[PDB]
Length: 251
Ligand SMILES: O=C(NCc1ccc(Cn2c(C(F)(F)F)nc3ccccc32)s1)[C@H](O)[C@@H](O)C(=O)N1CCC[C@@H]1c1cccc(Cl)c1
Ligand SMILES: [Zn+2]
Image (cartoon, protein in one colour):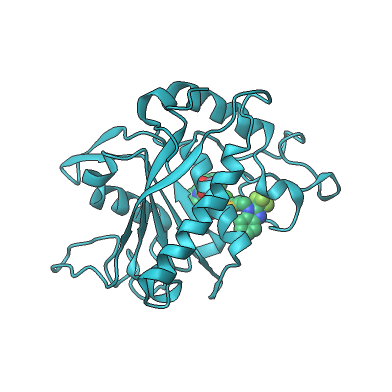
């Protein structure tokens, strides 16, 4: 491990929904929530031995927090991830998750090119219990250009998002930590843990599921906060390939 190239710096964005419903319309409350969450998620990453040996001490650090206090004014037929209305169905509380991630990546392209990852924190009730989305596991850590034919410019796939609202209520902080861990897990290169690999998807008596399980099943079992051997193997290759590219020294 290179201690000079072990941290993935983050651009953290809180939208107007997050600022209002999680930040109680205050900058201090918004930022304190995000600062503590990322630090707790960083403890999971930094304490993980990706090769089950000495390849550890890799994590994340906030470089900047962009706080969007109010909705983005849009011209007719124009869209933006921070606009007041959901897209494609404005009658719904939330965007289609995949479209929101594409939109966020488009709008944040200039800033995303200068950071290891960009993460959007929102407060919207996605359909069928979805809590987040991210690129990787193409995309993930270190900006990789994608020419958007619709958008007519390069966008970067070093992005992900977390919503702290599910089924009409604010999720617990212990649950939000797992969402962000999981989405950043995809950014770091991990796929979902499959049922066919018992080592990677244990029973409840064996400590439960690991963080990369596709379903936010529990939140109270030991393994829930940890990466499976399947995730470690995938992430191990990514860090080996990407740390030199965009990782920095821990501040
Ligand atoms: O919303 C998602 N995950 C959130 C989580 C799943 C499990 C996590 C941790 N976790 C666990 C526990 F797992 F530890 F138990 N118990 C938890 C209890 C509370 C909170 C978190 C918890 S967070 C999607 O996976 C998304 O990232 C994705 O890839 N998606 C989204 C759409 C397309 C694609 C997609 C692609 C293929 C299949 C699906 Cl389901 C979705
Ligand atoms: Zn996932």
